[PDB]
């Protein structure tokens, strides 16, 4: 097939799979890079270096303690033992979002992610590549120069809805009250396991819904650009609906076991008042979903 300093303030780190040999199709490899600095640094850019022939997708996470110590591992074992803050999502034939000017992820120091964990997913494998080494990964741009806007993730996950067997349509709803400084959403990622039909994200302010993003979870799960970023402010509600099918299923499915309904909202905040991670696992305002826009029920 290390560390490259660019100027006084900046430097570049590339996180590459260490010459792995995926044997078969639909296989996920995970690896880790500890952060070279112990002071706070800002990830301000990404360069993907994926072999076009065999790599379906790549995920970059930041987390305090990862799932394995070895040069690489299967991500079926896990990504991080702790919160995996997703930093980067690349998919073949997918728009990779470019962070807006002056946006950087805060890493290192007291609060910031200690490690990067790289996930590479390989979907198309020839059996006449029984011993070919791949060094797939991404290049990260770090600066110690402080950024005015800090990127972070609002993770919306449906902790319990059950899909009754054979129900053609089942709705998974998540809502939380926003009680922080203003967050500006520039991207979103939706995740689900093959019963999902559509995932839609909304800001609700004074009973008026504003769309963040709608996607089919069966498509490439990259980060989709929010064409005009949504401002989410204190006293707003974030509401999300996942649509599922119970069709063809013998038993009830759970959303530990079975299904997932996850919405990833990528945002920026003024550095002064910024926090990197927020989560919602509640549906505080269930009654409100009657008034949900009709678009949210329209499939893709
Ligand atoms: Cu999942
Ligand atoms: Ni191990």
Image (spheres, rainbow, N blue to C red):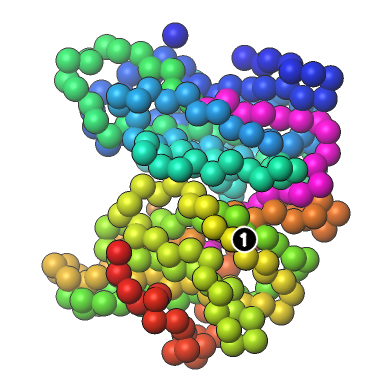
- Could you say which is closer to the camera, residue 193 or residue 184? 184
Residue 206 among those drawn in magenta: no
> In the rendered view of the protein, which quadrant contains the N terminus?
top left
| Residue ID at (35%, 77%) | 297
Q: Is residue 17 above or below residue 266?
A: above
In this view of the protein, can residue 112 be seen by the observer?
A: no
Residue 156 among those drawn in magenta: yes
Task: Pinpoint residue 98: horizontal percent, then vertical percent.
Answer: 58, 41
- Could you say which is closer to the camera, residue 225 or residue 10? 225
Q: Is residue 15 above or below residue 101?
A: above
Residue 133 is drawn in which quadrant? top left
- Could you say which is closer to the camera, residue 246 or residue 233? 233
Task: Pinpoint residue 158: horizontal percent, then vertical percent.
Answer: 46, 69
The region drawn magenta spans 138-158
| Residue ID at (38%, 22%) | 51
Q: Secondary structure at mark 1?
A: strand
In the displayed structure image, the side of residue 290 where residue 178 appears, left or right = right
Q: Disc 1 marks which residue?
A: 229
Main secondary structure along the magenta-highlighted residues: strand
Task: Pinpoint residue 22: horizontal percent, then vertical percent.
Answer: 31, 24
Q: Is residue 263 above or below residue 95?
A: below
Mark 1, Cα crowd under 10 Å, few <14 / some 14-19 / many 20+, is: some
In this view of the protein, can residue 190 be seen by the observer?
A: yes
In the displayed structure image, the side of residue 99 where residue 158 appears, left or right = left
């Amino acid at each position: 097939c290390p560390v490259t300093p660019l100027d006084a303030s900046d430097f570049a780190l590339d996180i590459r799979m260490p010459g792995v040999t995926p044997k078969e199709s639909d296989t996920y490899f995970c690896m880790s890079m500890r952060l070279p600095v112990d002071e706070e640094a800002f990830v301000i850019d990404f360069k993907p270096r994926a072999s076009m022939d065999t790599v379906h997708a790549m995920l970059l996470f930041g987390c305090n303690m990862p799932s394995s110590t070895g040069s690489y591992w299967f991500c079926d074992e896990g990504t991080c033992t702790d919160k995996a803050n997703i930093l980067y999502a690349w998919a073949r034939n997918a728009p990779p979002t470019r962070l807006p000017k002056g946006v950087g992820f805060r890493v290192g120091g007291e609060t910031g992610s200690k490690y990067f964990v790289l996930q590479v997913h390989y979907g198309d494998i020839s059996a006449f590549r029984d011993n070919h080494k791949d060094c797939s990964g991404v290049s990260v741009h770090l600066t110690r120069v402080p950024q005015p806007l800090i990127a972070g993730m609002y993770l919306m996950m449906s902790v319990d809805t059950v899909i009754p067997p054979g129900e053609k349509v089942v709705n998974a709803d998540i809502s939380c009250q926003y009680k922080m400084y203003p967050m500006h959403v520039f991207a979103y990622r939706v995740h689900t396991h093959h019963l999902g039909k559509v995932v839609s994200g909304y800001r609700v302010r004074n009973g008026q819904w504003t769309l963040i993003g709608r996607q089919n979870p069966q498509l490439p799960q990259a980060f989709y650009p929010v064409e005009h970023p949504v401002d989410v402010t204190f006293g707003d509600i974030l509401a999300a609906r996942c649509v599922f099918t119970g069709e063809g299923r013998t038993e009830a499915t759970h959303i530990s076991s079975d299904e997932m309904c996850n919405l990833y909202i990528m945002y920026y905040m003024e550095a002064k008042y910024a926090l990197s991670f927020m989560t919602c696992t509640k549906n505080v305002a269930p009654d409100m979903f009657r008034t949900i826009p009709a678009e949210a029920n329209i499939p893709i």
